Image (cartoon, rainbow, N blue to C red; front, top):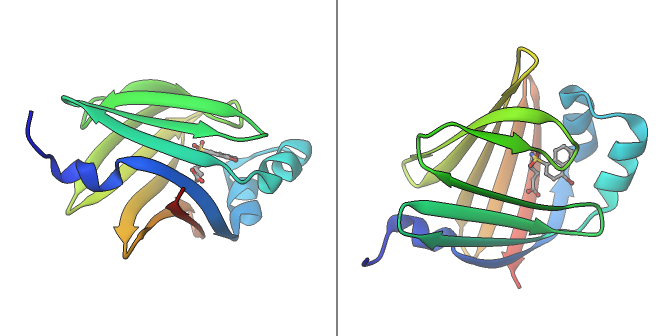
Length: 136
Ligand SMILES: O=C(O)CCCCNS(=O)(=O)c1ccc(Br)c2ccccc12
């Protein structure tokens, strides 16, 4: 295959800043101990594309996770904080939009390229967290 617009996400990324993530996790329903340990994590994210399949891997001292998916096609995800969710990821004008649904709740995670950074915006109801990754 030739290039895909999704190739702009491809690579190895490291978390350099996090804002409001504790309050985001609170809104999501994450328990005290998990929030404290998860909040300390400075994960590496490795994104790759192979045909129609996109893979996002996260490695940290908190948890190692991996999801593989096709855009617009719902899949089962066990999140880092051990929620069992139904996830659908789509592209909207260059932005990967990831919706997680569980227990009648919903949260949206947007991943976008901004300058040389990968910016992750997590929203749960009225609460937004911004996490910024740089190339590793
Ligand atoms: O990848 C990031 O740095 C942003 C976090 C994405 C949030 N959704 S998640 O289920 O993949 C997730 C990923 C990583 C951590 Br640490 C989480 C902690 C609490 C709740 C969710 C967490």
